[PDB]
Image (spheres, grey):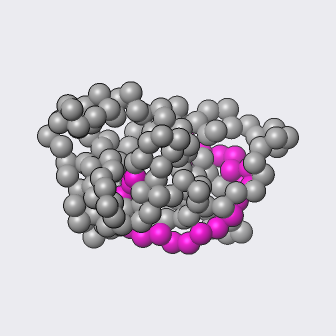
Amino acid sequence: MTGMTNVTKLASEPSGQEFLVFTLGDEEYGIDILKVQEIRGYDQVTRIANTPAFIKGVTNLRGVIVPIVDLRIKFSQVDVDYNDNTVVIVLNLGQRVVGIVVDGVSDVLSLTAEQIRPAPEFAVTLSTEYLTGLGALGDRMLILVNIEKLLNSEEMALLDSAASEVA
């Protein structure tokens, strides 16, 4: 998984995956297609009074609720606003669910570990242990969201003020 030491020995890596790709501000991103739960809109984010600020709030997916995380807060995005950050992508992992606010889903594309080598490891708010990756796609580039360790690495901090028993 991405985060640190993504040297890519290219010896037992997945070496060909497919990703839902999205836009925010003036940058593009990908997320492994299998982890996508659904796509929805920002019209019911519910910022709890004392959730961690990374959690913009919980929001309504098509029958249930999910925690939603702000890339302005988690990754120092340019200019998130309720005209540029109004789509929601909903994601699920092993035994848990989360999502992120987005401008729109740009495409669905396929990438290889040979592409997925760098990361946006600048002085952004995004900590190393759930740092994303970067790759190229002919001429496009995508920040590959480290979804398979995102909520996994944050759960202990997320639930501490977002388990609903703590609202």
Label count reads 0
Residue 118 magenta-drawn? yes
Q: Residue sitting at 47 percent across and 58 percent down?
A: 37
Q: Residue sitting at 47 percent across and 49 percent down?
A: 92
Q: Position of residue 36 (x, y in %)?
A: 51, 58
Q: Residue sitting at 85 percent across and 40 percent down?
A: 11
Q: Answer whether residue 61 is visible to the viewer in this image.
A: yes
Residue located farthest toward the right when viewing the structure as drawn: 11
Q: Is residue 65 left or right of residue 120?
A: left
In the rendered image, the quadrant that contains the C terminus is top left
Q: Is residue 10 above or below residue 87?
A: above
Question: For this rendering, which residue is in front, 85 or 121?
Answer: 85
- For the record, the magenta segment spans 99-124
Q: Residue sitting at 48 percent across and 40 percent down?
A: 95
Q: Position of residue 89 (x, y in %)?
A: 42, 60
Q: Answer whether residue 114 is visible to the viewer in this image.
A: no
Q: Position of residue 51 (x, y in %)?
A: 23, 37
